[PDB]
Image 1 (spheres, rainbow over the protein chains, first blue to last red):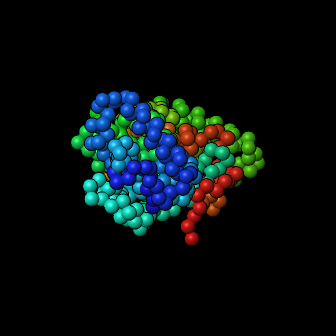
Image 2 (cartoon, each protein chain N blue to C red):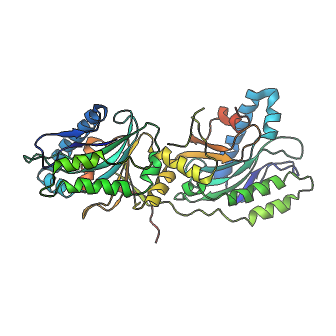
Image 3 (tube, rainbow over the protein chains, first blue to last red):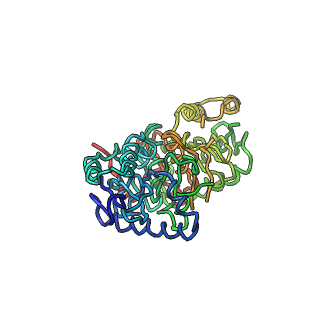
Length: 211
Length: 220
């Protein structure tokens, strides 16, 4: 586990534990979505951003480097008033069971939410945050069901019981996709969102404003 | 609610009950294309493969045949005068039914359906009893998590259980899943096609043969 983004106690971008193969594309994606949403919401942006939900996510291999990625992202700010989210992320193997993770117990994500939220107490120590994250376990995520591609167009899974078949379908639904869920807020209802790929920049405001 | 279509040993012609043509027309054309392509590919080897091939349980998305979803079991079969065609028992479901929980749910309905199809191979089962049994058969225990759009798919899933069920339903959309106990030649497992199996893929249901690229490994 590592983190990347802005914290109120520091003026610059801060990042620990994450390679550039994640951070570069992640930063670019957030930056584009930050600007598009600003253009769209204009004067109403700040109020939307500052009350928006923390978002738990699971992103399939190949979207942000070769590894799968899970974590939580929270609206944040630096020491000098510039806005940008704070993200705690764990890189997982390409055969990770994102299915069971999205459909799994909430506990890892609640632990990450608590850490992130803590960074918005005035007396927050950034080095205390950096250590908690550095001492943070990966989430309980096992290997996905054995699968092969046969003659270009059949996916065969070694699933022989009802539980294994369910697991294999859910795992498949995560491939090539990003999944976003969590508690929502008083403007956005708790629920799950899937995008094929990373969300497009103009879809970024949907993280901030509901219907 | 359940019906059947195909051939069985006790009747000389095609037999169909309880199923609309919306299903049968395409289902027939798809089996026939498959039969013909598997036959061309396999040649003299075809009949041996066919006769000993598995019973395949399936769940098919809405709009790949007619506009209902379909679940069932299909078995290699034959008519009273020796011509080959599969026998299928099929239940048509609402286009919004949860195929995920069915593919990933209790085997019981499917095992019951397989026992009925198997009964028709017995010299000499009464055809009337098979039809009666199929007609008395309940729908499977399967209503998908509420979802909408904005690219974006929002599911109304607020618990890990609901998120798991949402993900599994999504893997079924636009797809056909085929699974079962296998045979001496094909291991038990699960198969997915985007859409219906292409006709030249029909053969794989009889032989399990293919160019295998491993994607994700087994665990010790």
